[PDB]
Image: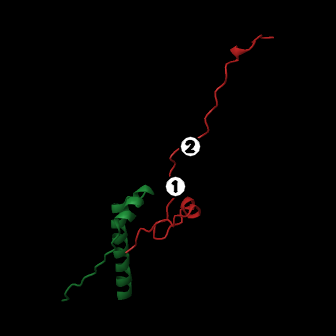
Chain colours: A green, B red
Amino acid sequence: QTAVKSRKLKTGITVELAQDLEANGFDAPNFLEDLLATEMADEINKDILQSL
Amino acid sequence: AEIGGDHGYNATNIAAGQTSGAVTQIGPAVMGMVRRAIPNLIAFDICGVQPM
C-alpha cells in the first residue's frame, strides 16, 4: 500500500509573445499546451526509468 | 517566464529577425511596393507631325 504523489508544472507567457507567435504560424494556445504535455510525459520517463 | 522580447529597432536586426527574447521572427511582412510615377508627355500637335 502506497499513497500517491504529485508532479506539477507551469510555464507562463506574455500576451505580446502570444500575439506575435500567431504571426509566425504557430497556434499559440495549442502550441503551449503541447509543451507541458510533452515535458510532463517526458519527465515521467526520467522517473519510471530511474525508478527501475 | 519566456518574455516575448522585441527587435532592438535596428534595421540590421529587424530585417534578419534577430530578437531579444524568444521565438525569433521568420521575417518582416510585405506591405507593398512603391515605384516612381511616369511623367506625362506634351502632345506633339503643337508642332508639325508629318509621318514619313
In screen coordinates, is B41 left or right of A31?
A: right
Classify 10 Å Cα crowding around label 1: few (below 14), some (14-19), many (20 and above): few
Nearer to me, B36 or A5: B36
- Numbered mark located on residue A36 in the image: none
At x 61%, y 35%, the residue is B37
**First of labels 2, 1 by sequence position:** 1
In the picture of the structure, the residue carrying the numbered disc 1 is: B28
In the picture of the structure, the residue carrying the numbered disc 2 is: B33
In screen coordinates, is A8 left or right of B47?
A: left
- Quadrant of the rendered structure where residue A1 is? bottom left
In screen coordinates, is B6 left or right of B12?
A: left
Q: Using the image, name the chain to which the residue with label 1 belongs.
A: B
Residue type at tag 2? Met
x then y, percent, for residue A29: 33, 62
Nearer to me, A45 or A29: A29
Q: Is residue B32 above or below residue A2?
A: above
x then y, percent, for residue A28: 37, 61
Q: Nearer the viewer, mark 2 or mark 1?
A: 2
Q: Secondary structure at mark 2?
A: loop
